[PDB]
Image 1 (cartoon, each protein chain N blue to C red):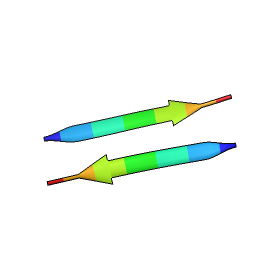
Image 2: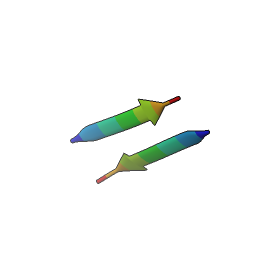
Image 3: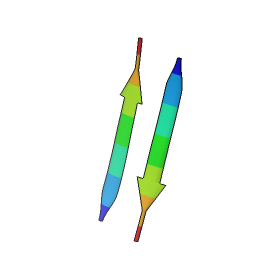
Image 4: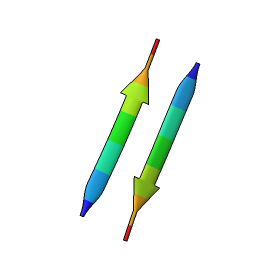
Length: 7
Length: 7
């Protein structure tokens, strides 16, 4: 499993 | 901002 968030 | 989670 992989999660990325960028803002 | 930056967030990563791998499992």
